[PDB]
Image (cartoon, coloured by chain):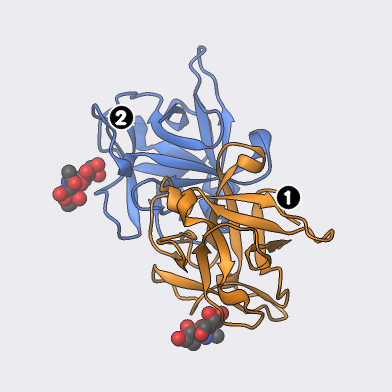
Chain colours: A orange, B blue
Amino acid sequence: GFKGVGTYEIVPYQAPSLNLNAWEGKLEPGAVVRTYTRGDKPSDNAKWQVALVAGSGDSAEYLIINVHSGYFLTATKENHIVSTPQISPTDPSARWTIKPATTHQYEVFTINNKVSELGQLTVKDYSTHSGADVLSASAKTADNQKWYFDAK
Amino acid sequence: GFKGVGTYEIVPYQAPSLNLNAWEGKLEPGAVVRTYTRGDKPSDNAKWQVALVAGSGDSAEYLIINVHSGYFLTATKENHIVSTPQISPTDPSARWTIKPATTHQYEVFTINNKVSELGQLTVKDYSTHSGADVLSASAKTADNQKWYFDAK
Ligand SMILES: CC(=O)N[C@@H]1[C@@H](O[C@@H]2O[C@H](CO)[C@H](O)[C@H](O)[C@H]2O)[C@@H](O)[C@@H](CO)O[C@H]1O
Ligand SMILES: CC(=O)N[C@@H]1[C@@H](O[C@@H]2O[C@H](CO)[C@H](O)[C@H](O)[C@H]2O)[C@@H](O)[C@@H](CO)O[C@H]1O
């Protein structure tokens, strides 16, 4: 479950054998983000430090920081793949609110950009297989916009 | 004053016309950190996002993130200059506790590395002039190890 700041796998609701993965797991900035197979031991490029930067409660604003690279999960354009560029911690495109979206008692959450037009973290075309683009897309709390936070 | 997460100038107690500055203010990783003249408007390389990553209270652990570059304030060696390298948010050398050290009613704090041997954020040789090396040095809560957090 999501219990605030900590290190997590971020796991798509429709495909819980997958997690949120900084593609290629390199140290250079600007990686795109996709779903990928979790594996028995998740790799550091697929772990994320949720770090509080403003507020408290459901309105709290967080950076979602890649464990391997230290770069921040960022939305760059509506209905477009998200990435981990080098970017200021005060840039709202790199800040996210995490909101309960419990579904049949599954403790899942939406991940909502501080720039409201950039919307929610979204698995492209509702894919249930490894390697799907993760988008910032218009917020609807569809099933492909829901996520588990598995504490690590 | 320090009131938790937010963007701050971090100001040395002995020289309050100065602040903590990522030297050269470039985007490449690995800048060393020094005191430098604040100016009328502080520059982004001399502003820091304090971001909560674990715990609560005086024991809370924070990243101290450069506003300009997004790299984390890090201690690398005892009694050595501190820097902002590319580094994982889970590395304890990049995590700090901020502890009250009120002095004659001045609201100042110590900045203490999570790796206890790396010690406290320290103005080399108690300098009161711009351009002094900021070290990670043995923790004594000396006056050159005390800091204001001016909210920005
Ligand atoms: C094991 C390893 O490091 N492989 C490198 C590749 O990294 C993987 O990339 C996939 C996506 O193709 C995925 O992100 C996975 O989590 C990564 O471990 C990749 O960097 C490759 C170059 O394209 O080099 C491999 O050595
Ligand atoms: C105004 C500006 O950007 N100047 C550049 C220098 O940056 C300053 O560097 C000093 C330390 O010498 C200090 O960190 C200050 O805050 C910075 O603005 C520096 O990058 C210089 C190359 O060494 O280029 C200047 O253009």
Instruction: Please name the residue shown 73% across and 50% down the image.
Output: A3
- Alpha carbon separation for disc pair 2 and 1: 38 Å
Q: Nearer the viewer, mark 2 or mark 1?
A: 1
| Along the line of sight, the residue nearer the viewer: A137 or A151 | A137
Q: Chain of mark 1?
A: A
* Residue B21 marker: none
Residue type at the position of mark 1 = Lys
Residue type marked 2: Leu
How crowded pointer 1 is (Cα within 10 Å; few <14, some 14-19, many 20+) is rated as few
Residue ID at (73%, 74%) = A16
**Which residue position is annotated with label 1?**
A3
In the visual, does B122 lie left or right of A68? left
Height in image: B5 above or below A65?
above
Res B21 visible = no
The numbered mark at residue B18 is: 2
Q: Secondary structure at mark 2?
A: strand
Location of residue B113 (image quadrant):
top right
Q: Residues within 10 Å of mark 2 (few under 14, many from 20)?
A: many
* Residue A19 drawn above or below residue B98: below
Height in image: B12 above or below A26?
A: above
Query: What x and y, as percent, mark residue B14?
Result: 37, 23
Which residue is at the front of the view, A90 or A137? A137
Discs 2 and 1 lie in a common subunit: no
Please provide percent x and percent y for residue B131: 25, 38
Element carrying mark 1:
loop
